Image 1 (cartoon, protein in one colour):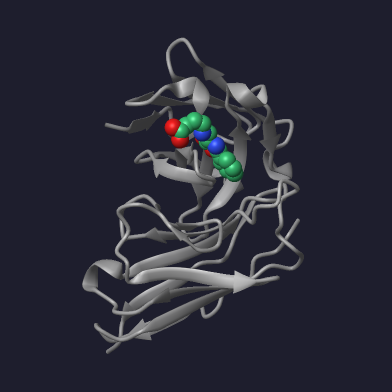
Image 2 (image 1 turned 90 degrees about the vertical axis):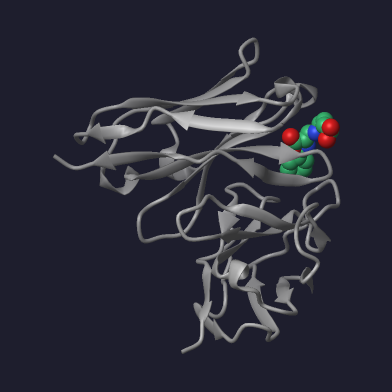
Length: 113
Length: 121
Ligand SMILES: O=C(O)CCCN/C=C1/N=C(c2ccccc2)OC1=O
């Protein structure tokens, strides 16, 4: 089981600030076909998860371009350049390269008090 | 256009069983991967089962956790995904979600609203 370590657990932000979430796989995540199936998800309160980025870096259609993903080896980062109220929720990174497929523990992006 | 609607959750005592359903429309079913993911009330999304499209022989892959207790299947005539769950227990109580892949290389590009499963008498 490839472990996905997500950090931080809680990321308090102010609307309009940049924000970075990171992941850390315990082994390579390169599928045998060559692709790295690393995606990012966003679960808003009460809603079902939504696909943000796939294959480490490809922003899914319809997703605000303030979202972007990157990384190499076992380090992956999901960046939000300008946090909007609608971006508040729980983010999950996920690897779908090696079985069993694995999510990170989640990162709660919330309003900073 | 793309629709996924789960159904089959409920309240059940330990050791019992249920069959989840995932009705879909808006796309040619047989050509996409389908999956079941659950989220216990605290907690983190957890991948459970997955089944590929026709071009991949409808191959499946299970999470050890539900191995030999859960079984996924798909009715291609009706475009419906199912999940037979046996010998249920506390750690199985959660919201279950069905999801379909993306042709450009993504799992769970679309999710159903999910149904609830509560175990514990
Ligand atoms: O996008 C096209 O219209 C569709 C035809 C076939 N696309 C199949 C799909 N390919 C995959 C998929 C999912 C995870 C890793 C790599 C590929 O999931 C799908 O459902």
